[PDB]
Amino acid sequence: AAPANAVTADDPTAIALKYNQDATKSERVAAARPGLPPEEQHCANCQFMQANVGEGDWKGCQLFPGKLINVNGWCASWTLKAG
Ligand code: SF4
C-alpha cells in the first residue's frame, strides 16, 4: 500500500518523466540514461533520491516536492548518485 503522498499515475510530472514505482515496469532500457547500464538504474541509486525524507521503501525525490517515490522505482530523470 503506497503512502498517501506517493507519486501516482495521473501526476503530470510523473507522466512526463515516465515514472513507475517499480523499475521492472519502466522504460529505463529505451531511455538509456547515462551513468549505468539501464537495467541497473532505479531510485535508490539516483542523485535526486532524498535519504532523509520518508520511511522504508518510500523516500523523497527532489523533483517531486511534497511526495514520496519508491526506492525500487525509476523515471527518465534518473541520474547516478554521485554525492
Ligand atoms: S529522479 Fe531519480 S529518485 Fe526521482 S523518481 Fe526519477 S529515478 Fe526516482
Image (cartoon, rainbow, N blue to C red):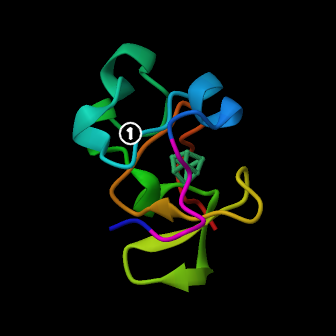
As rendered, which of 56 and 76 lies closer to the eye?
56
Where is 30 relative to 15, above or below?
above
**Residue at disc 1, secondary structure:** loop
Q: Is residue 10 above or below residue 60?
A: above
Q: Nearer the viewer, residue 26 or 66?
A: 66
Residue at the spot 59% in from the left edge and 60% down from the top edge: 82
Position in image of residue 38 (x %, y %): 32, 32
Q: From the viewer's perspective, is 80 left or right of 83?
A: left
Q: Which residue is mark 1?
A: 36
Image quadrant occupied by the C terminus? bottom right
| Residue type, numbered disc 1 | Leu
Instruction: Say which quarter of the image contains residue 27.
Output: top left
Does the magenta-highlighted stretch encompass residue 33? no
Q: Is residue 27 left or right of residue 68?
A: left
**Percent of width and height locating residue 23:** 31, 42
In what quadrant of the picture does the N terminus appear? Answer: bottom left
Please tell me how many numbered marks the rendered image carries.
Answer: 1
Q: Is residue 7 magenta?
A: yes
Residue at left offset 56%, top offset 52% = 7
Q: Mark 1 near ligand 1 (CB under 8 Å)?
A: no
Seen in the image, is 58 located left or right of residue 78? left
Residue at left offset 54%, top offset 60% = 6
Q: Residues within 10 Å of mark 1 (few under 14, many from 20)?
A: few
The residue segment tinted magenta is 3-8
Residue name at image x 64 percent, y 57 percent: 48
Q: Which residue reaches farthest top?
A: 30
Outermost residue toward the right in this view: 65
Most common SS among magenta residues: loop
Percent across and percent down for residue 61 are: 64, 60
Nearer to me, 32 or 51:
51
Q: Left or right: where does residue 26 sit relative to residue 49?
A: left
- Residue 14, horizontal then vertical, whole percent: 60, 36
